[PDB]
Image 1 (tube, rainbow, N blue to C red):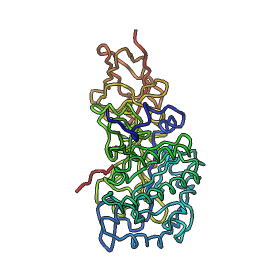
Image 2: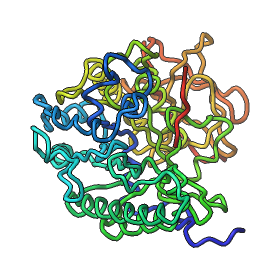
Image 3: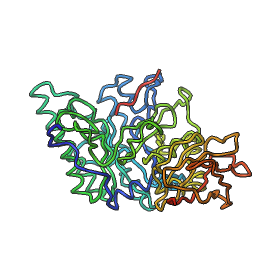
Image 4: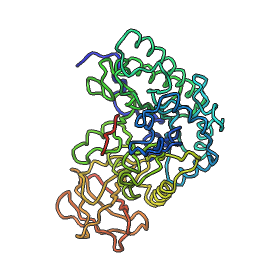
Length: 446
């Protein structure tokens, strides 16, 4: 194997209580809010179909001009308590907030740049208001942080010269300053989710990624750090040159998920997927007619899919420039909330069950060996096939919502037909088993 100084630090999954909490939470919301919310995908009369938070790029807007949006940053309708209540009602156990996106505008009053909420008409420390309000609802807060920073001229996409190295070294010190400031100002932070770390400049500075992970872990006891931050000595990202996962959890499943039959490898490590409601919009885009918009059942399927393979899922929201959420997101949060209130026993604190995937939907496993069948696709046969691992029997099935007994018929050794409920639940539903020992598009840049 390749000798490395800045490759993986963790052997298996972390099993300290902070990581157990990170994992058990399972369902999170992503909040993308920044200057991009103001134009909302439109510049000088032209609507661009690309992701709204990348509008500076699509519309070729110079840094000085883009950041002049600060003069219009005045989210009059913002209420952090209302944001927190929305998340609580959705059943989210944590929220990941954009502290600073690629544009470089900070949602907290950083001492290290003038491009912050302090220098807008609104003035208020948005991030601090959100941290307090979410925590008051018993919701953990995670910080999204973009290393790539379009507002700082010391940023480099690659290191091609001595000057480049000089400028980028200053940039990395600036980045450390902001990160230390976040960690110490808001010590209840549970996770740093890095983004914009794919450029050759960061790949050439794997040492710094390892340094940033350690620096934050020393400042915030038990903090989690995503794989997206990390590059090894050789510039290899997420997993090092010896195939070992860097950081605390894998973070490359973006608007896609691992295959339930072919990608069981993912059960070996902690991981967190993220997703958008439209095809590819993270920040506020004013026109959702431009791409397909997922229904609530489509989103719920993806949430359960992640949990069934041992991962977390984070559903994105892109708040309006005024500080409210658009009606489509309010509808989505309420719909997810309703379902989670009924069926969340099968999601929270659940994990991969070790059973062969069946067509009716997903298995999940509780902390105390409860096995849950989450049914998305109702069989005309009126029979849900369950093939158990060797040495496992099914002793009972119970409908989660009503507690009613569900008929279980052995069809052959290790195989059963679980009956569908006598009355069709009319939505994706859960059967709890008692088991026993026998005897045009753009790909996500991540």
